Length: 48
Length: 49
Image 1 (tube, rainbow over the protein chains, first blue to last red):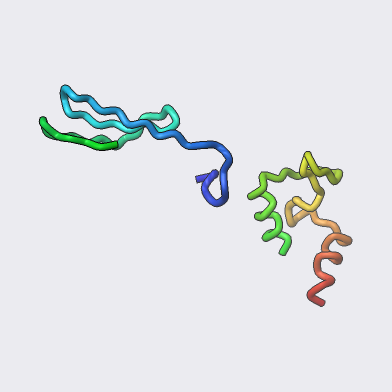
Image 2: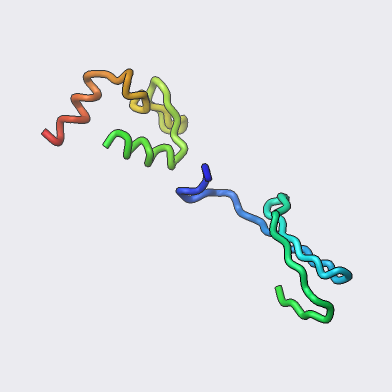
């Protein structure tokens, strides 16, 4: 919230992790793990 | 007007100071209202008169 309100100067990196054995989906932002996750079904095709 | 300029400057990450600087972006104009100066107030209020 402090940074929001103008133009920053540091790039934002978002990482997405896929587990092909249990169908777990996680997302990390700048090395910080988010609190949002997704669950998929076996035999599911996903495109980045 | 003073607080609008101050907000624009803190958008640029300015800081309060005594002397005027360019790289240090310090100025005595970023001060609380309870400790302003008569000269600065007169200069700021002159244009609207």
